[PDB]
Length: 240
Ligand SMILES: [Br-]
Ligand SMILES: [Br-]
Ligand SMILES: [Br-]
Ligand SMILES: [Br-]
Ligand SMILES: [Br-]
Ligand SMILES: [Br-]
Ligand SMILES: [Br-]
Ligand SMILES: [Br-]
Ligand SMILES: [Br-]
Ligand SMILES: [Br-]
Ligand SMILES: [Br-]
Ligand SMILES: [Br-]
Ligand SMILES: [Br-]
Ligand SMILES: [Br-]
Ligand SMILES: [Br-]
Ligand SMILES: [Br-]
Ligand SMILES: [Br-]
Ligand SMILES: [Br-]
Ligand SMILES: [Br-]
Ligand SMILES: [Br-]
Ligand SMILES: [Br-]
Ligand SMILES: [Br-]
Ligand SMILES: [Br-]
Ligand SMILES: [Br-]
Ligand SMILES: [Br-]
Ligand SMILES: [Br-]
Ligand SMILES: [Br-]
Ligand SMILES: [Br-]
Ligand SMILES: [Br-]
Ligand SMILES: [Br-]
Ligand SMILES: [Br-]
Ligand SMILES: [Br-]
Ligand code: NA
Ligand SMILES: [Xe]
Image 1 (cartoon, rainbow, N blue to C red):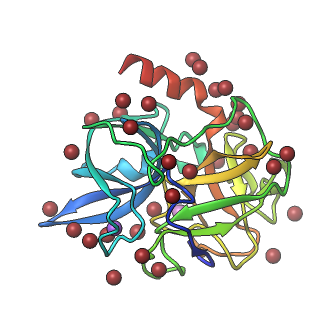
Image 2 (cartoon, rainbow, N blue to C red):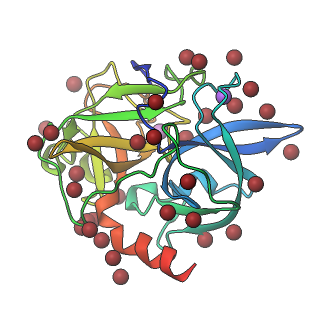
């Protein structure tokens, strides 16, 4: 997250860190949203590589013991069947991860609430992106979970020439684009939290930014729109 502020430890308890094994260590690569005690929602592109993945819930500082972490292996990966890694613009950038264990809930670990199916936010609805992604274009991961305020940019504007043109689909949410604040690499897979009738819901799964840079004016961060996938999510969870 570029132009973020440090999140309070208990503000976003459904946020997870998706990490891959690297030698005797683990490295953060993406975010995710805990949606059942044993299921995480993330981006399909995050699990394109066939690595060993683990999920950390109750994570705040990637570099220090927070005293609240639960470390759980990824047991099963169900990527959206229409996803194509060489066509992120087509959308379908969503995957579910079944965890090896069911995590224990507490003020640092809660389920993310999802929007009602087919819900579309009005232009300029306020949202926060959260993540440990790069804090500058071509920078480094954050140590502590960041949040940044990114208002939505509706399909008509986001798909206009000055913005993302044909790259953006109605199955995506655009948010941000002020040139200061944005998602960035390593935020992929994580949530876009937006208020609806007084409650935050996870409306977006971070999918991509401009090749030009993370915080680029009129290149808002682009998210998979969760409310286009409610039936898909329920179907996977029901069969698995
Ligand atoms: Br949350
Ligand atoms: Br390795
Ligand atoms: Br480690
Ligand atoms: Br890390
Ligand atoms: Br549950
Ligand atoms: Br469970
Ligand atoms: Br900290
Ligand atoms: Br560090
Ligand atoms: Br540590
Ligand atoms: Br495990
Ligand atoms: Br698998
Ligand atoms: Br799969
Ligand atoms: Br529990
Ligand atoms: Br609690
Ligand atoms: Br608390
Ligand atoms: Br909703
Ligand atoms: Br629904
Ligand atoms: Br829809
Ligand atoms: Br939306
Ligand atoms: Br930091
Ligand atoms: Br335009
Ligand atoms: Br396209
Ligand atoms: Br669409
Ligand atoms: Br759609
Ligand atoms: Br990424
Ligand atoms: Br990264
Ligand atoms: Br309201
Ligand atoms: Br509200
Ligand atoms: Br501009
Ligand atoms: Br749906
Ligand atoms: Br359903
Ligand atoms: Br269906
Ligand atoms: Na930590
Ligand atoms: Xe990203």
